Image (cartoon, rainbow, N blue to C red; front, side, top):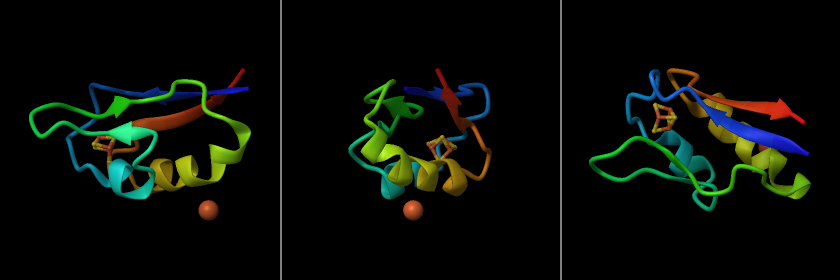
Length: 65
Ligand code: F3S
Ligand SMILES: [Fe+3]
């Protein structure tokens, strides 16, 4: 039970999140990051932390619900 949060004022479009977890983050060429699942399964928490770590602006975050 967690939610993937994106500080959209901080996303500069590096698209490192899509390279680390492509199933859960998609970045349009002309758009910022799009969170495909806001409430992903518990098995996906590992690959999503990769995207949180790999964001140079730290726009992504995991919030426990
Ligand atoms: S800048 Fe944006 S495109 Fe992803 S790697 Fe960080 S949330
Ligand atoms: Fe890992």
